[PDB]
């Protein structure tokens, strides 16, 4: 079961065929709180990109 | 040298998959968009497009909120090389989370149509792309040839698979094709349309994108290539494309004077010889 | 995003100027008493595109300044019965040539009168 964050999406061009992206801790925690969840529940879950 | 675009997007299917969209439009065959206008669009406070990418004839836009009502955002493009042929371009809009939910729309030049003209009827869908013929008033103007203006056109450079002398009764329109309802007085030449005879009705179609016109009441001579579509009654239908001989037959009212009577004599010699003899030479 | 506009016997000429803080495609509209306002002309952002009303084809012209970011509109060969309140309006989404009244943050306009 996949639960996407309605936000946090990235739209970047490609330079030399590679693009470097990252998810900051603050925005990730904000997204988690908006999903009614805490960082303790991330036991068997995986981040799907 | 420049043209202004306009992109309107909206969704009426909010029940289904919703969210954002990626609007990928393809500019015309030679144009390329201005980066300044798209940058002005993106750098707004209440920005409507959140991301863009322009390269040659390709423009990519990212809309973060597809509304329900019309919302048009426009920009500008310049021209690099001339447009070699008339053609409609494309513009696709994907769904961000499920790109398989797309919508592709064809659009045309600032004056042309969005789809290629085609004569379609039941099973047959004969093409009607190219040039449209002219109304050559050879008899009205002064010119002379040795059985070459019409006999050569019918037997040497082009090969006309059909030829009739018809009377124009009614004018009509059907989609992008102007329709002329005519009746055949006498049959001059035929290959496939064997059933054609006197007092038989036929339809002539001409693209409505040029100036050709057939006035009612007048009598014309039609010659050209045989078509492939059929009328609603099951009879062949002809398309007045290029390399087709159309000429109004004089009614002898403006021919009795000495100068044009020789041209009328050349005419009658032509029609009689072509009707009685089968394209000699 | 505010618009400021400033600027005669028949057959003469005039030059209105409208100044805006933001550089965009501010177009011109005309409003006469007792009837709905009708456009007169429009210009794109860069200024290399202009359209004019059919009644004023080849008569009125618009230009723009790249320094102070204002639109200039010259009306040589002024027609006697064109009297109306002139407005300069614009939108932020660059809908060039949008004839119908869908321009936001409308201007205040100036009253210009013409005597035969
Ligand atoms: Mg031969």
Image (cartoon, rainbow, N blue to C red):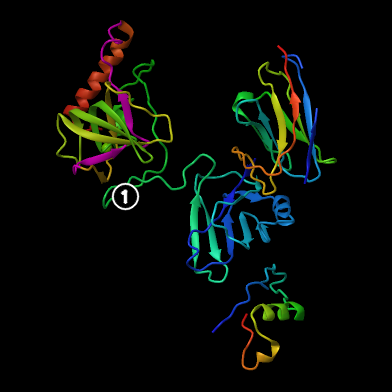
Mark 1, secondary structure of its residue: loop
Q: Quick one: quadrant of the C terminus of chain B?
A: top left
The vertical placement of B98 against B48, above or below, is: below
Picture quadrant of residue C55: top right
Identity of the residue furthest to the bottom in this view: A43
Left or right of residue B179: residue B86: right
Residue C98 position within the rendered picture, expressed as x and y whole percent measured from the top left = 61, 40
Residue for point 72% across, 81% down? A29
Provide residue B103's location: percent of width, then percent of height.
49, 60
Report the predominant secondary structure element of the magenta stretch.
loop
Task: Tell me what residue is drawn at x 31 percent, y 26 percent.
Answer: B150
**Residue B4 falls in which quadrant of the image?**
top right
| Residue placed furthest toward the top | B257
| Depth check, front residue: A43 or B143 | A43
Q: What residue would you read off at disc 1? A: B125
Q: Kindly identify which chain the residue marked by label 1 belongs to.
A: B
Instruction: Tell whether position B27 is magenta.
Output: no
Q: Is residue B18 left or right of residue B244?
A: right
Q: Residues within 10 Å of mark 1 (few under 14, many from 20)?
A: few
Residue C70 placement (x, y as % from top left): 80, 38
Report the residue at 60% width, 47% height from top. Answer: B5
Left or right: where B277 falls relative to C77: left
Residue beneath the point at 36% across and 18% down: B144
Residue reaching furthest to the right: C67
Q: Farthest residue in the front direction?
A: C34
Q: Looking at this view, is B274 or B256 the one in front? A: B256
Residue C52 at least partly seen: yes
Q: Quadrant of ligand 1?
A: top left
The quadrant of the picture occupied by the N terminus of chain B is: top right
Q: Is residue B239 magenta?
A: yes
Q: Which region shows up in magenta?
A: B233-257
């Amino acid at each position: 079961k996949k639960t996407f964050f309605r936000g946090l999406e990235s739209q970047t061009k490609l330079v030399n065929g590679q693009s470097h992206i990252s998810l900051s801790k603050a925005e990730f925690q904000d997204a988690l709180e908006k999903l009614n969840m805490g960082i303790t529940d991330l036991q068997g879950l995986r981040l799907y990109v | 040298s420049r043209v202004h675009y306009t992109v309107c997007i909206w969704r009426n299917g909010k029940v289904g998959l919703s969210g954002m969209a990626i609007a990928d439009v393809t500019l015309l065959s030679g144009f390329h968009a201005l980066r300044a206008d798209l940058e002005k669009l993106t750098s707004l406070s209440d920005r409507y497009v959140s991301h863009f990418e322009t390269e040659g004839p390709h423009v990519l836009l990212y809309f973060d909120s597809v509304p329900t009502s019309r919302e048009c955002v426009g920009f500008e493009a310049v021209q690099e090389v001339p447009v070699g042929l008339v053609q409609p371009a494309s513009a696709t809009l994907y769904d961000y989370y499920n790109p398989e939910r797309r919508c592709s729309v064809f659009y045309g030049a600032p004056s042309k149509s969005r789809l290629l003209a085609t004569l379609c009827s039941a099973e047959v869908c004969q093409c009607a792309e190219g040039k449209c013929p002219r109304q050559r008033r050879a008899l009205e103007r002064g010119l002379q040839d040795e059985d070459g203006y019409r006999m050569k056109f019918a037997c040497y450079y082009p090969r006309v698979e059909y030829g009739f002398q018809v009377k124009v009764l009614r004018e009509d329109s059907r989609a992008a094709f102007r329709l002329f309802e005519t009746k055949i007085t006498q049959v001059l030449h035929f290959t496939k349309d064997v059933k054609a005879a006197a007092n038989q009705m036929r339809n002539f179609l001409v693209r409505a994108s040029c100036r050709l016109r057939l006035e009612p009441g007048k009598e014309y001579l039609i010659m050209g290539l045989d078509g492939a579509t059929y009328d609603l009654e099951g009879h062949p239908q002809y398309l007045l494309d290029s390399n087709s001989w159309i000429e109004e037959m004089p009614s002898e009212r403006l021919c009795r004077s000495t100068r044009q009577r020789a041209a009328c004599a050349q005419l009658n010699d032509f029609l009689q010889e072509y009707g009685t003899q089968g394209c000699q030479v | 995003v505010q618009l400021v506009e400033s600027g005669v016997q028949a057959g003469g000429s005039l030059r209105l100027s409208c100044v805006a803080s933001e550089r965009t495609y501010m177009a011109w509209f005309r409003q006469a008493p007792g009837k709905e306002r009708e456009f007169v002309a429009a210009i794109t952002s860069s200024g290399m595109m202009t359209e004019y009303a059919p009644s004023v084809k080849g008569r009125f012209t618009i230009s723009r300044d790249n320094a102070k970011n204002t639109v200039y509109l010259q009306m040589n060969s002024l027609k006697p019965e064109d009297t109306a309140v002139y407005y300069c309006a614009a939108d932020l989404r660059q809908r060039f040539g949008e004839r119908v009244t869908e321009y936001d943050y409308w201007g205040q306009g100036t009253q210009v009168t013409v005597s035969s």
